[PDB]
Image: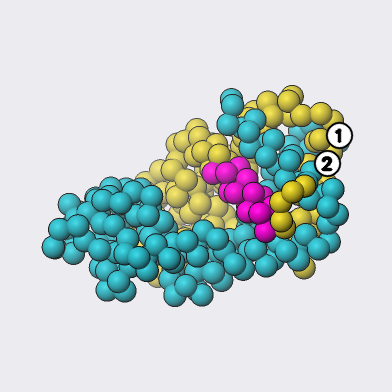
Chain colours: A yellow, B cyan
Amino acid sequence: GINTDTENISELLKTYWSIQRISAGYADQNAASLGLTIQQLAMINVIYSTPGISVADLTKRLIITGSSAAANVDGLISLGLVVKLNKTMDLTLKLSKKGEDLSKRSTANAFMYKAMMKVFENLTENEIEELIRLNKKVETLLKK
Amino acid sequence: NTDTENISELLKTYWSIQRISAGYADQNAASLGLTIQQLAMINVIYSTPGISVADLTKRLIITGSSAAANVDGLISLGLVVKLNKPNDSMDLTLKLSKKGEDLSKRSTANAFMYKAMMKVFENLTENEIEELIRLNKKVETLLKKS
């Protein structure tokens, strides 16, 4: 390899960024198939992880405005995907059964699997094994 | 492993690396004095000089009010320049100043991500590094085909 560690790092970071950008498109399609925007889906997922979370904390955790978060919350309540834990930014929420079912469905992204499946048909078994092992090595080395 | 299990493993690993990269992106933003949203705006304006505030909001998928506040902030900091002197207008068009270009560049070339990857590379062989890059590049190329 002629290139420096620095040029190699750039190439790797550009490559990962490009994969992540393509992956975001498939993440959009998966959201769309559930009838939601990616932002609506992110909100449902936060509420799934943190039942009883307040709107104030939900907003901050999504890094969005209160007016847009309050509109989005209102929209998810309209769809029967979330429920108010007190029906009297201080509002607390949890998912309805319908909200949980969609959140779970979102975990399996059928669009990304079909796409990666096509990629694998054009990789050798040794490349697949190595691709997995080397990225996992990078991940683990990054974690420390 | 079955192919389905290998796809899952890869996708989880990529997701995890992206999660780690995001944390370094936050450190970098902090070092540039800007929020991630401020840098996202800077980066859009860099690739599309003369973009309108109306279209800037739609591309960032943000409120009109926030976009207008954020835009006036970037003008206060000397990072963007109006192409016709009303700061809160949706019809306002923008380009980055020189200093805006400089920080955009430092945002894309994340020095904290690089140092982190240099330490990773120290625990990888010259052959592993070439294959990591080659195989990931192959994956990207094949994704772009279908």
- The percent position of residue A72, horizontal first and vertical second, equals 37, 53
Q: Is residue A37 above or below residue B101?
A: above
Instruction: Note whether residue B134 is visible.
Output: yes
Q: Tell me, yes or no, whether the highlighted magenta stretch contains residue A7.
A: yes
- The percent position of residue B88, horizontal first and vertical second, equals 19, 62
Tell me, yes or no, whether the two marked residues, 1 and 2, touch with CB atoms within 8 Å.
yes
Q: SS for tag 1?
A: helix
Q: Of residues A64 and B54, which is closer to you in this image?
A: B54
Specify the amino acid type for callout 1. Answer: Asn
Give the chain letter at badge 1. Answer: A
Quarter of the view holding residue B7: top right
Q: Which residue is mark 2?
A: A130
Q: Tell me, yes or no, whether the highlighted magenta stretch contains residue A115.
A: no
Q: Is residue A103 above or below residue B25?
A: above
Using the numbered discs, state the Cα–Cα distance from disc 1 to disc 2 in whole angstroms. Answer: 6 Å
Specify the amino acid type for callout 2. Answer: Glu
Q: Is residue B35 left or right of residue B95?
A: right
- The percent position of residue A77, horizontal first and vertical second, equals 40, 50
Instruction: Note whether residue A72 is visible.
Output: no
Q: Of residues A51 and B63, which is closer to you in this image?
A: B63
- The percent position of residue B50, horizontal first and vertical second, equals 26, 51
User: Could you tell me which residue is drawn at 60 percent across and 49 percent down?
Assistant: A14
Q: Is residue A129 above or below residue A49?
A: above
Residue at far left of view: B85
Q: Which stretch is magenta?
A: A6-21
User: Could you tell me which residue is drawn at 32 percent across and 60 percent down?
Assistant: B96
Q: Is residue A95 left or right of residue B66?
A: right
Q: Dot 1, crowdedness within 10 Å: few (<14), some or many (≥20)?
A: few
Magenta stretch, overall SS = helix
Could you say which disc has been placed on residue A126 in the image? 1
